[PDB]
Image 1 (cartoon, protein in one colour):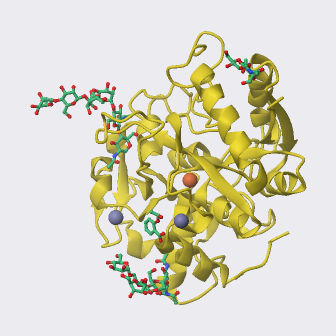
Image 2: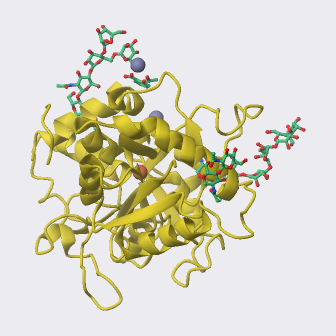
Length: 341
Ligand SMILES: *[C@@H]1O[C@H](CO)[C@@H](O[C@@H]2O[C@H](CO)[C@@H](O[C@H]3O[C@H](CO)[C@@H](O[C@@H]4O[C@H](CO)[C@@H](O[C@@H]5O[C@H](CO)[C@@H](O[C@H]6O[C@H](CO)[C@@H](O)[C@H](O)[C@@H]6O)[C@H](O)[C@@H]5O)[C@H](O)[C@@H]4O)[C@H](O)[C@@H]3O)[C@H](O)[C@H]2NC(C)=O)[C@H](O)[C@H]1NC(C)=O
Ligand SMILES: *[C@@H]1O[C@H](CO)[C@@H](O[C@H]2O[C@H](CO)[C@@H](O[C@H]3O[C@H](CO[C@H]4O[C@H](CO)[C@@H](O)[C@H](O)[C@@H]4O)[C@@H](O[C@@H]4O[C@H](CO)[C@@H](O)[C@H](O)[C@@H]4O)[C@H](O)[C@@H]3O)[C@H](O)[C@H]2NC(C)=O)[C@H](O)[C@H]1NC(C)=O
Ligand SMILES: *[C@@H]1O[C@H](CO)[C@@H](O[C@@H]2O[C@H](CO)[C@@H](O)[C@H](O)[C@H]2NC(C)=O)[C@H](O)[C@H]1NC(C)=O
Ligand SMILES: CC(=O)Oc1ccccc1C(=O)O
Ligand SMILES: [Fe+3]
Ligand SMILES: [Zn+2]
Ligand SMILES: [Zn+2]
């Protein structure tokens, strides 16, 4: 009657999608691809309907016709009387994080160090820090800036993948999906935590959700926030409590996208699904919780409170904002209307 095919990236997302499919009585069904870009293509072909995307991918999807439908909303102190689904989004803070013990490392001495990125093309892990680095160095050779990195989605034989570890068997090194040990917000933070890299380009929230006992993961259980510092654009180092005055930029929240012609439909189904498996849902945590995967951020971020309606009914450019869009455009000149497929 009103059924939606979700696109999952990699085997772990596929498994979560299947459980959701099952519990939804197949109001939702699953398609799987190895990368986010491949999922976008399935959506364009009409073989999948939707998936939730980081803003860097929304820019890609947007140029090819896809539109934002609902956005991730997390916990807030302000707008509190308003229901989550109607509450305006706030965005997240992109930060650069280092170990306190790595003394004297600042924004201005990052050259030739080792970096941990969520994935190529993502907002906090790539577009913001590389855009800044390209601007302040006046060169498009962002591949020669760090000595070694893990940036999932880059050429596996390049320096940008040297620090990537692949899966439990060493396969799939540097793939941009959760099979890669250092992929995503959690993987990049882990890459820093294990001292594989000197700096991780993540979001403020990641630091908090993976320290001081907030995560039981064996690599994270003994991590304390005091052992980390944020790098500020002014060359200072600050504690992680100061992200409001020490971030690289404010990113637009991850959002669900779909083909324009399927948007109304996707929106209707998802609003019903979250009533069922969302934060206060009929069936979470009883049977299935859509916004939980045990700090793995599968399909949606684990800190998501709800998916919220947009309003003003954005175009992708308005959703991302003119500040962010010009940032991406300029970075992309190193590698304006065309379809990347
Ligand atoms: C970086 O990322 C991290 C991780 O995402 C961010 O940290 C997180 O922030 C949230 C809150 O923003 C944490 O949430 C929770 O903690 C709350 C505090 O214990 C819990 O209780 C409150 O929840 C309610 C929200 O609905 C709110 O309740 C009210 O607060 C009023 C004041 O704001 C209060 O009024 C009294 O307040 C004062 C008392 O001393 C007096 O001055 C006043 O006169 C008055 O008496 C009301 O009575 C009422 O209680 C309130 O906003 C609290 O948040 C809540 O249940 C929940 O558990 C979240 O845990 C936390 N994550 C982690 C891992 O720590 C961080 O903010 C980010 N940083 C940046 C810069 O963005
Ligand atoms: C790397 O460097 C790149 C080169 O600088 C950089 O590219 C871009 O950098 C600028 C930031 O986007 C951009 O400048 C524009 O400035 C104006 C911003 O004005 C509006 O916003 C302000 C918000 O802070 C408000 O205070 C003002 O009220 C104002 O509204 C542009 O907007 C105009 O706004 C007013 C209307 O109020 C009006 O006069 C205009 O009609 C228009 O609406 C203005 O047009 C500039 O575009 C700059 O153009 C752009 N540079 C290039 C070459 O594209 C990139 O951001 C850097 N990368 C990173 C990651 O930092
Ligand atoms: C599968 O989707 C359908 C459509 O939303 C759901 O069936 C609806 O049940 C509600 C609850 O009263 C009614 O308002 C609708 O009229 C029903 N739709 C029709 C006309 O078939 C069903 O709840 C969904 N199942 C799950 C588990 O998500
Ligand atoms: C509010 C929405 O339409 O757009 C924005 C929000 C912040 C900054 C810029 C924009 C915009 O449209 O450019
Ligand atoms: Fe992101
Ligand atoms: Zn700021
Ligand atoms: Zn508009």
